[PDB]
Amino acid sequence: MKLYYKVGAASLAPHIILSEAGLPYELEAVDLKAKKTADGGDYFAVNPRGAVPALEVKPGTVITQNAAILQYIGDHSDVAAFKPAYGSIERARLQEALGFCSDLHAAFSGLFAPNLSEEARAGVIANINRRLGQLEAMLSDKNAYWLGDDFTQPDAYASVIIGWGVGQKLDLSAYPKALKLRERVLARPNVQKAFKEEGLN
Amino acid sequence: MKLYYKVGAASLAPHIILSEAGLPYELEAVDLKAKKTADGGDYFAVNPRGAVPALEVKPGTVITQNAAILQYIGDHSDVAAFKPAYGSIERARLQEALGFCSDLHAAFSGLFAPNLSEEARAGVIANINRRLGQLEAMLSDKNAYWLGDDFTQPDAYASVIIGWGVGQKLDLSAYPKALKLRERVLARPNVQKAFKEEGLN
Ligand SMILES: N[C@H](CCC(=O)N[C@@H](CS)C(=O)NCC(=O)O)C(=O)O
Ligand SMILES: N[C@H](CCC(=O)N[C@@H](CS)C(=O)NCC(=O)O)C(=O)O
Image (cartoon, rainbow over all chains, first blue to last red; front, side):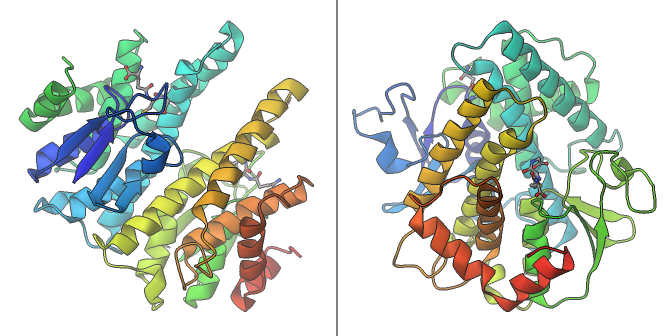
């Protein structure tokens, strides 16, 4: 399969999960400014919504939307935690966490919008603070990772988003459970392998 | 199961799907202003994120996030279209459409925010127009419903969101495929049954 990604963007989540699954994959860096693939072609032909990630499962079949991509990879892996039975409460918890990741992502996205005024920026920060508080409350110290004993796709996606906060030098020390989850994810060897593949430290 | 809903809100989507599935369900109207259940209790104890829908599967187990709720209902129904195999391309298409519904929903949500300035409102309208254009392009006249020959959860969710546009008297006549999908959904008897259950016409 082929993952369309931009360095450090939300596409790092499925990059991490592809690496953890150990399935063969190819990567394609997208220029999101010009909306072009690396050969100079039109990225809108790949994803008409214009976003990364997109996953080409095989020629002519491209899946968009992180929740879909993350679960497709999981269902085609051998990692049981990545692929709970549909209809099981575990599957619902997986989807619920991925849905919340989209909400968390949406709060952060406001921060990188162009011509962002200081006043508009304050509202973005307030929503980031609100979503981070909700993630923090949702995490339980009875669980090594978000959903329980096992690392799953949500963990990777939350860790990437929190990393955007780190990169922006936001103070996230009031969210120790969130920081601990990210620290745990960042130490996983297949996570480091994905970060390397994007030229990131 | 028990669905926590507000009249005409995004919770109408799983209300529709519960009705279509024919499984037994109870409804609970939430006051989102006071964040209270109808007995006067704290809705944050039900969903700490404060949103509808929430689905109590059984006492002590509440699922939040529309994508999770919609797929839980589908996986516990007898309707094959609602429950494609995990890992099948059909399941990925289902999740992709639900993920896009969240994006469409997010564009519309801006319109109902309090103290919305005329200028901020224009940007909201521009994003609604952009997301509606993307939905329109994603729909294919080869398909009776969004994903193909079969009505699915996405169809209900898109139809509810478009309905918010109708209620706001936005001109959506440049999106005929979207309008046709909604018209088709609104004529389904179990859809009308759900609308009735919320006191809606
Ligand atoms: N500054 C970017 C952060 C990644 C990023 O901002 N990308 C997207 C998410 S993939 C975003 O946060 N906002 C716009 C968007 O989500 O498309 C980087 O270091 O790569
Ligand atoms: N005016 C509301 C529209 C529904 C609504 O606006 N609810 C939510 C979605 S459920 C929304 O569009 N914005 C805030 C939110 O999504 O919570 C109604 O007629 O019920």
